[PDB]
Structure formats: structure tokens, C-alpha cells
Image (cartoon, rainbow, N blue to C red; front, side, top):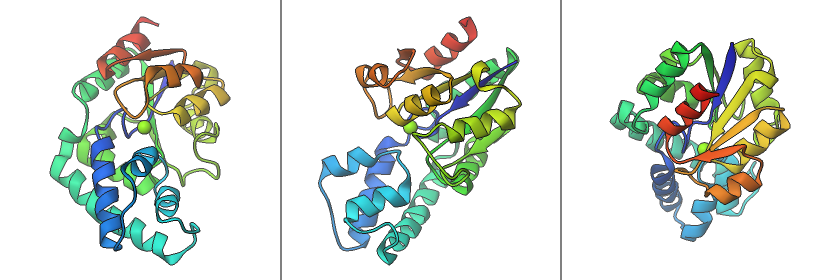
Length: 217
Ligand SMILES: [Mg+2]
């Protein structure tokens, strides 16, 4: 009777490299380019805000919508090409083990909700997850607690009995702010010290290790 709230990019789905590459493809389509470090700094964060920051324009600039739509096309094609291969090894099996032990599972992603659901459907996450929320599901996205509180409500589990698993500082900040335990993972966008400094209770180095941490309590 406990909840596990999982980030998508860099936690369940091995997408950081594809996100960086497709971001670059989209900027090239828009006739431009930015530093590698700038792109890397955005990986896994909300997409329109990230693209606006890389282009150096207001988020409401029409160039942002153009870039976001092009990104959606390219990323959607990538996800259809990958299917379940989009996920890190052990993810579906791990989620099944958590379900078997009586945990209710949710996704909380900085992707928009429609994209999150489509990815869940193409990878097989959909049959494991009770609730899916994205950046547009709530007024205040990561690092605010709201998304985690919203999915906890969806699960019917009080925040106190939920754990957040993610690879980003925003996930750790979201979980801590929501009054939840946080398991950071080091195989995504963040190193372990940064996650500990952001409030992770522990940091593990693989998804199966995160599952073991939850199962053993
Ligand atoms: Mg992430």
C-alpha cells in the first residue's frame, strides 16, 4: 500500500542521447545551432521552455512552437523505431516486481502528458502504470511538488507513503517538497553528489538497484 513515482527521461527511458541529438536536428532545421554544453544543460527538462532558451527567444515567440512541433515529429519517429528498446534494461521486469510486492506505480515527467502516454503505450510502460502526469498536467511543473502530489492523489496513496525515483535535480526537489522519500539514479543526467545535495535520500547506479532499494524498504 505504497506508491512509486518514476521520472521518464533518464530514469525509465534511455533517452538523454537521443534528446540531445534530436534537439540539435531541430535547431539545424530552424537554420541554427548552439553550443553542445547548452543543449546538454536542457536534456530532460520541459521542451518548449528548453527550446526557447536555446533559441534565445521568449517562450511565446512563434519560432518556439515551430521548433516544438518539429521536435515532436522527430522524437515520435524515434520512439516508434525503438519501441520497448527505448527503456533501460530491467525496467519492465522491475516494475512488474514492484507491482507484485503491492506498490502502485506512476509516471511524473517533464514531457507533455500526450507524449508521455504515447511513449508509455509504445514501450509497454502503460500496462504497469496506474497514473501518468506530464508538465502540462499541472499548473506548476518540476521542481514544484505539485505533479507528485497530483499523481499521489491519482494513486490514492498519501504523499508520506510515496517514493520518487529520478535522475534529475528537479525530481529530487519535487519529491522533497512533496514530503516524499527520493531515490536518485546516477545513470541519467546527474551525478551522485548533485543528487545528494538536492535532497536525495540515496543514489543508486541502475534501475534494478532502485527496485531493490524499494523492495527492501
Ligand atoms: Mg529525467
